[PDB]
Length: 336
Image 1 (spheres, rainbow, N blue to C red):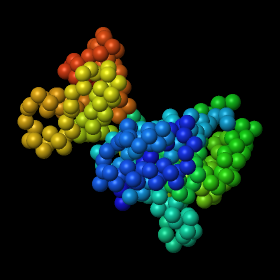
Image 2 (tube, rainbow, N blue to C red; image 1 turned 90 degrees about the vertical axis):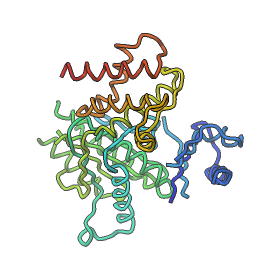
Image 3 (cartoon, one colour; image 1 turned 90 degrees about the horizontal axis):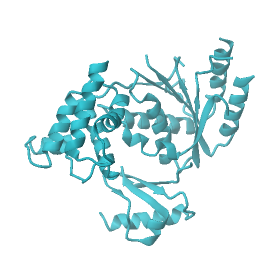
């Protein structure tokens, strides 16, 4: 189908019925695009964004010791999903796998006949956004399952538990959130003796519940029925990442004035020929090629370094910015 994500304003107390009614009628007048300004006043009042990304998901964002807790969908994770860029379709695959995992628990499929369980292992080299993808994935499952779960919960356990009871108090609090069966509960552990044994025993207990999924990451438990390698970005991915940063700096008028930037597709479409818009993306494509082997984490830090080291003013040109970024990629390599 087509998926339409409807961000309702924090302040709004309008019912989803009306948001739903009104947003379908908006889509009749316009037989993937994001809307931020609307003709109908009810929309401008109640709705921050409609986003083709026909099923509607309407959500509001929400704003324990040795764990971070978030009610999903969380303000902190808004845009996290779109921010993460992989060579292959890992994101759409993970979403599909965890969603059939949850259909199968719902309908109580015997896991002895068809193998499935509610634990996910993202593994691979560091700087890859494995933890951000676990968060991004929790957010998106929560948004897409509003018709089954009223809200979600995320508990990120700190494997800074190798320090000097505690564990029984944490999992008791976690159990209290699990008891609410309107809530899809995610428990996130990054990989790393009687204490370790106690958390592993506690995971085994909570992993029994229908509404619990265990997200795990490894820079390398052991029985997760969905394992997924997440590797570093290629030139194409690096181009998308950099382009999301330049667009964000033109949104915020740090890069002034707005110039149009072409995507790698859009410049394949015109056979890479140089005009006065397309030359800025031809330069990005060179900067991308000379960035390959850097992690997503370094890539999303580079536009900050570029600005701090090589751009004085509150504003700078797209031509000015790409010069600084180019310089920033060189400093990154000349240090390592």
